[PDB]
Amino acid sequence: GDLSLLGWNTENSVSFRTMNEFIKKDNLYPKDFKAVYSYRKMTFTATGTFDSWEMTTGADGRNIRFKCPIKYAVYDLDGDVFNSSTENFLLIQVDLTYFDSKTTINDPTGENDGKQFNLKIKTNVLIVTYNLTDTDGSMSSEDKDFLSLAFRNWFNENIQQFEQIFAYILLDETAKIPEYQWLKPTQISYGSASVETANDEPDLDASIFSAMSMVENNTNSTPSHAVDNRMLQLTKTQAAFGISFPLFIEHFLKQALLSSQFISVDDIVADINTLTITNNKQIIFGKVENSDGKNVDSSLKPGKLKLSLQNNLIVLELFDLTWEQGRGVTGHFDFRQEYELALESKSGKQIPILKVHDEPEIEYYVEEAQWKTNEDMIVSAVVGTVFSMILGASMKLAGSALSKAGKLIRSKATTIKGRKKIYINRSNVRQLRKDSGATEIELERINRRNSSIAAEDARLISNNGTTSIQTLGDMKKKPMSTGQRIAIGAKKIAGTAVMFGAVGNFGEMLINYINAMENNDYSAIPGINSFMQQCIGAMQWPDLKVTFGKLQGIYLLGGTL
Amino acid sequence: SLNINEDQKSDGGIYDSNFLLTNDEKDEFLQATVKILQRINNNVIGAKLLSLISTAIPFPYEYKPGDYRQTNYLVSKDNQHYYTANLVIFGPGTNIVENNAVYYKKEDSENGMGTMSEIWFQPFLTYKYDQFYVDPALELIKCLIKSLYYLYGIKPSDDLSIPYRLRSEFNSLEYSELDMVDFLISGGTDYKLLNTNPYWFTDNYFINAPKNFEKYKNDYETKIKNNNDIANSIKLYLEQKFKTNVQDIWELNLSYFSTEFEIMMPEIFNNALNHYHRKEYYVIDYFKNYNINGFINGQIKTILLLSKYNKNIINKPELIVNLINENNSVLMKSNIYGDGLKGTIGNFYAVYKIPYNIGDEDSCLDNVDIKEIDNIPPINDADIYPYRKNCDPFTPVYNITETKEINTTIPFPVNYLQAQVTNSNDINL
């Protein structure tokens, strides 16, 4: 249904035309050929010069198909001399293996301590379909078959003359930036997938030749070379990079959730199956200053602070955030937020930016008795708690807007399973944002303050991405609204996305990215190029600008050479 | 091609592009052909004919002095296996009632070397002549004898053809003349008007053919028989082929096999039947209406189901006779059909020159030894060196009949014959 890597993590894909141009520039293919076949007292010869080879449609998985046109050839069929036409060609079938070779490539983004593997044809070559005709149409089908046998004998004998190197890979090379070892392949592979056109012609553009590779010593016991054909067709780019969602989650979402100070290093459990990062035990979300003036611990149940990928969106969820609000009243709130990693063209540069997408979803559950007995009184404290989550701060507001929102709040009350439930959809969130009365400038000021305090938290954050419980208590003991805590957590999570934004304690580099996202200073930040460098330092084509980036089952980037 | 244009259809021929298509039909054809082969082989003379065809390999072509390459071979799909075959029996071509035999190479089958033969055979259909059904085994025998003519390289020049009939239907002088092989092997009463002692009709072909046979016999016995470059199987096959001369092949005809096999066949103008006998076809079930002894319960007492193809018989007549009255009103119309024989406008009898000076001097296949031929081991795939240009490019030949009209004030016999048939079931004679 979508793009699948069938056990692999990283992938680099190109079109057939791009590889054909690589072969054309490299010019490491045989030109002159002399095929000879001798059998049953009969001798057949095909001596001539080949044209430039073209890798066309017909290759799938391990199979690699190349079109070899013939510039001019002479055929000797037991003395029968024939001159081939200029339209004659053959379709050879070969396979690719990453043979180890002496190091010749350089990786400025790596330590160059790995081993160079070059893609070459294994030691054989079979021809699938050919076209061999003379200038007068006097050839016979058996003559053409015999010449095809001679060509097969030539290609098996003369495969060594094709000294073309298909690709270069650095294996087990330590990255120059230690934090991004996930961008250095460990176990590599290739794949092919060719797609025909409507007019039944080889599509040198839509066809996709890929190279899959595991990273960070991930064991793959099922080496497969099948490649999804729609990986390039959607992008319409000459080259593409692909990073698996499992690596996007087990090495990025863990940092975002742990750095949010809501969980500790020993209270986070990775879960590949559900593609969600959460807390194994009950945690604390922050300090709550209700309308009663008493500081309350915001306790989250295990498995509720969720961070996952849904609907091509980074989804952050909170559930079962329960405490004692006052006079023996308990209510539960649920929140869901959607974010999208898009690409923005700023100052002539492609900058990956995480931006809000659609509107959040809210749920609130309470007992019937509280509604029937103390509906009016507890509503004040509930409002004081809720307004923080919306405005990002716990500030009072006029009662006219309170009644205007309260009529809608009481309108959306339903009775399910003996409990009062209210649901807030996408439209109600934007309605609340418009009716809140807080200008976007004030929100930007809040964002600046939260960015500065998130830089302070990252200073408190150790190398592993966690913070000591003593320092966590020192930071959290300060009285601050729960909405501001949500904003600080969001700021820290977004700042942790620099690893997918920029490649290269990490606290000061995060502070540099914070300066870039708060003052628009990317003078020392190359932007996406560094990340693209990590995708091309280890995967060097025989030589680009990246203009496409998205996620369709896989973090996918598209670029043109 | 299984489908041809309508005007390219041969008159009196049945065209069904879906015939012999499914695997069940192909298995039926295979079993029927094998059953007819067993029937022919069971008789002594048929067995001798089969052994002769099995041993009459075409003469190897000397590509180099002392280096001979076979002409009779079949190439596998991927061209690594070669099969020795003197004769391969196919199904019919475009027309499913046209039994025939064709040569692999023209010149090699004309000058004594010999070629492979390819047979178009229709074992499922037969026609009722007078009071009997023609045995398909006899048609297979006739095609086998034509294949013998091809294998021994004694095929005449295409222009050699004795006259057969006078086209008396037309108002013009024209003679329908039959090919030499067809006249030599058809038999019948017509063959009695040429096989005379002395021979009134002689041609250079009957002198040249034994010459070429003896020439290649000498070539074998001097060059080949003492040569170890080729397998002894080819030596034995050529020894058995040359053990029978061309006179024996000439005297083989359907009259002799009709006498030996006791098969009723047409005997008068039997190669010009398409003008006389507008055939009707019957389907033969070789598990029900045939066995090793021909038609079960005789050729007359057996019952055959009418074939579905009789309505599909193409009827393009050579003449349309229109009986008209004084006021030129079209009273009656009828079709007179051709015979598929080349019609010349010149009198053959007024041009032929009876040879004043000539020399005139047993069982037809007495010299053939079935036991000797059977004892020969076959030719393995590993000892076959083919010759590339052993096959002429096959070209289908389409006979284009011509249609002409005649207006008659006096009824012709076909007018009466067609007026005597009716489809109405309430008939007043």
Image: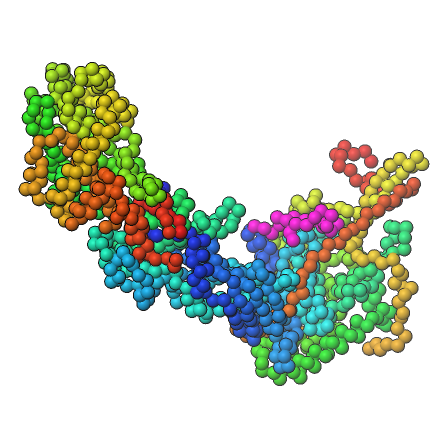
Q: Main secondary structure of the magenta part?
A: loop
Residue B15 falls within the magenta-colored stretch: yes
Rendering coords of residue B235 (x, y %): 61, 78
User: On the picture, is A159 further left or further right than B111?
Assistant: left
- Relative height, residue A184 to residue B117 (above, below): above
User: On the picture, is A27 further left or further right than A9?
Assistant: right
Q: Quadrant of residue A548?
A: top left
Instruction: Pick whichever, B41 or B379, lies toward us.
Output: B379
- Relative height, residue B159 to residue A528 (above, below): below
Colouring rule applied to residues? rainbow
Q: Is residue A55 among what the camera can see? A: yes
Q: Quadrant of residue A357?
A: top left
User: On the picture, is A414 further left or further right than B323?
Assistant: left
Residue at the (42%, 52%) spot, across then down: A15
- Relative height, residue B249 to residue A53 (above, below): below
Instruction: Pick whichever, B193 or A61, lies toward us.
Output: A61
Residue at the (24%, 29%) spot, across then down: A441
Rendering coords of residue A250 (x, y %): 22, 46
Q: How many marks?
A: 0
Q: Is residue B369 among what the camera can see? A: no
Residue A279 falls within the magenta-colored stretch: no
Instruction: Pick whichever, A557 or B185, lies toward us.
Output: A557
Instruction: Pick whichever, B355 or A229, lies toward us.
Output: A229
Which range of residues does the magenta coloring cover?
B1-22
Rendering coords of residue A206 (x, y %): 44, 48
Residue at the (39%, 67%) spot, across then down: A123
Q: Quadrant of the C terminus of chain B?
A: top right
Rendering coords of residue B144 (x, y %): 68, 64
